[PDB]
Amino acid sequence: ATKAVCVLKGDGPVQGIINFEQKESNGPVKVWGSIKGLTEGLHGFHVHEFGDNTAGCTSAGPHFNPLSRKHGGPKDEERHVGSLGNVTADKDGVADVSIEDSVISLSGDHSIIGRTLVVHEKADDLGKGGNEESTKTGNAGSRLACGVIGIAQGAGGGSATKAVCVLKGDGPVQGIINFEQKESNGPVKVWGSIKGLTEGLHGFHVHEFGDNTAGCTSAGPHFNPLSRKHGGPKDEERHVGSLGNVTADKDGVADVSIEDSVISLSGDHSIIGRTLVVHEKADDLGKGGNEESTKTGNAGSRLACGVIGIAQ
Ligand SMILES: [Cu+2]
Ligand SMILES: [Cu+2]
Ligand SMILES: [Zn+2]
Ligand SMILES: [Zn+2]
Image 1 (tube, rainbow, N blue to C red):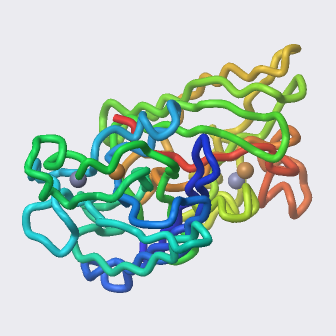
Image 2 (cartoon, rainbow, N blue to C red; image 1 turned 45 degrees about the vertical axis):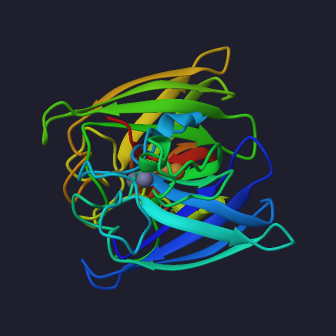
């Protein structure tokens, strides 16, 4: 895509929104926004390999590094793709970010879509610490906050054989959903657990944008690259993102087990860097006879969502 976004959150007070824009498909990426809750001074700022936040920032794995090079600073030949250097927080604990980088992309095998942006406790020494740790992390220390990099309203995306989504919302609904596609236009297995739901049927869809800047609202409509009407997963007439219903048991738990051949974890129907949403009400699978049925299945409000990240 030509635009991406990341909401950074952690166990402490660090939070922010970082925007990405890439106008020419392998030109430089503009990176800008704001992070607050930081100590005054320099903080390591990196793309890590996996958009897996199922164990906070730890499950993001190491720096994104397809080239197997040593850690470096940005404007520097020997670096990781994900080495974006340092952000500087002012005396109000705010880092105003304004970067331009040519090594990261929002498309291709060097795409950061569906990966994790991390802000660190300490400064990145940019590989010039002498020791071994410096040539892997820049001695940047703890991961204070992170988020999965999602597709924002523009354009695209990213590529993997496993993906994962951490669902959260305003209310008590939360869960983790796993995606596995062992052959690269075969079915995607979709499995996991969501809790805090009312007993019964809940609409379950991939929405177009991996944008959670305004909660689930900013995820936009159902992912619909073929411009079809909403349907059930078994219908010819459906959105790519229309995975049907999941069922919550009397304890409010939906043990999701789905297999879909229309979604993909690569190519132009890739759901990497898009948002998975679970809904208030049953999806009528486009059989409701009203205009809303043909758009959303009358599934109602978005109880929880998250950005679908590369796991594999
Ligand atoms: Cu990092
Ligand atoms: Cu939906
Ligand atoms: Zn690095
Ligand atoms: Zn739909």
